[PDB]
Image: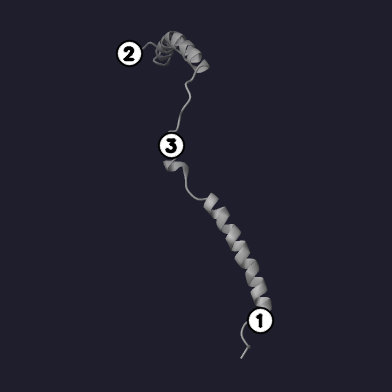
Amino acid sequence: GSRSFSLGEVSDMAAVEAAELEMTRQVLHAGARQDDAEPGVSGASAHWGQRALQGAQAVAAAQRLVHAIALMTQFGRAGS
């Protein structure tokens, strides 16, 4: 008996429709988790990185050495 809907209700409803449509974008960009997002794509050969790793290899001899004493110090050279 209302003679259908009022056009003002439709006007407000259209604002909600527009809002939901944009809200949908926000929730989609908030979707997914990095739990299954391991990287894989690669296409560049490390150049300067190799020189850094060559250093890492040379120093590793000193590192495995310092670590050896670090064990003796936490063991307090005990055992007997």
- The residue that mark 2 highlights is 79
Residue 20 is drawn in which quadrant?
A: bottom right
> Which numbered circle lies on residue 17?
none
Say whether residue 9 is left or right of residue 68. right
Q: Secondary structure at mark 2?
A: loop
The percent position of residue 68, horizontal first and vertical second, equals 40, 11
* CA separation in Å, label 2 and label 3: 45 Å
Pointers 2 and 3 in contact (CB under 8 A)? no
Q: Crowdedness of circle 2 by 10 Å Cα count: few (<14), some, many (20+)? A: few
**What residue is disc 1 on?**
6
Residue pointed to by mark 3? 38
**Type of the residue with mark 1:** Ser
Of mark 2 and mark 3, the one earlier in the sequence is 3
The kind of residue tagged 2 is: Gly
Question: Residue shown at 62%/62% (left/top)?
Answer: 19
The residue positioned 58% from the left and 61% from the top of the image is 21
Q: Position of residue 14 (x, y in %)?
A: 63, 69
Q: 5 or 36, which lies in front?
A: 5
